[PDB]
Amino acid sequence: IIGGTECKPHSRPYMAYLEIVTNGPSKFCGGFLIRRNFVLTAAHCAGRSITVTLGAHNITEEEDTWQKLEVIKQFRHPKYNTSTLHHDIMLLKLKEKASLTLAVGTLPFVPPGRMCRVAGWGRTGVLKPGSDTLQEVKLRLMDPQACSHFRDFDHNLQLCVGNPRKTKSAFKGDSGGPLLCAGAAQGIVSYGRSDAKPPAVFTRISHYQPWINQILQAN
Ligand SMILES: *[C@@H]1O[C@H](CO)[C@@H](O)[C@H](O)[C@H]1NC(C)=O
Ligand SMILES: O=C1Cc2ccc(Br)cc2N1
Ligand SMILES: [Zn+2]
Image 1 (cartoon, rainbow, N blue to C red):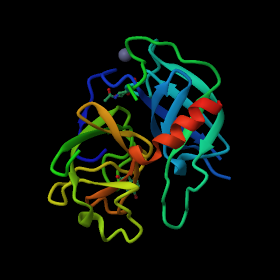
Image 2: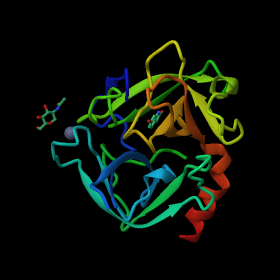
Image 3: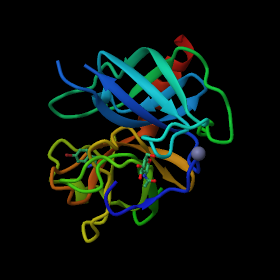
């Protein structure tokens, strides 16, 4: 998260920190708990295996709120496209149902000009390392023409997010985190420019609701 502030610890109890294993070292993403055994995230966060940590704030400092949970199966959207980046969404089924605590719970599951918030442990600058702590930033929902320069951007599939006159943005490591507008998840962090100049492109959750529901029922 670039240009954001540190969250009050545990104030976003649905947030998930993902460590993804592959021919290379671990990579990291965000995500969010939508059922006690399901986490929503981005398709580009798929790997050979994934571990989810719930209840975290400072991810380097173990505490009783932590629940480190095995993922049994990844459900990457079958149409996720590495060329166009369309359909960047994935469900992770946890081995067991998470415990509900003050620090861990599910997330109950908009015109441009509206302000939305996104949280994550990703880089706090283009050349800065990932954050030890959960950060959040408020971003402006933009008209789709604001994202025209992303040539494969599609208004039906995606949200255009972030005033270009502000430096505020999600970035590397924030992939998969929710964008909330009035407390409801509307987007998922997907991609943007390598120099972090806003706006960026988020998956429009509403388009994928039938696919999500279908997975939640077959599994
Ligand atoms: C997070 O925890 C580590 C280890 O306890 C500590 O070194 C670091 O300063 C902490 N970061 C913040 C911002 O609290
Ligand atoms: O919003 C985002 C998420 C993201 C991930 C990676 C890169 Br490079 C840029 C961005 N911008
Ligand atoms: Zn704590």
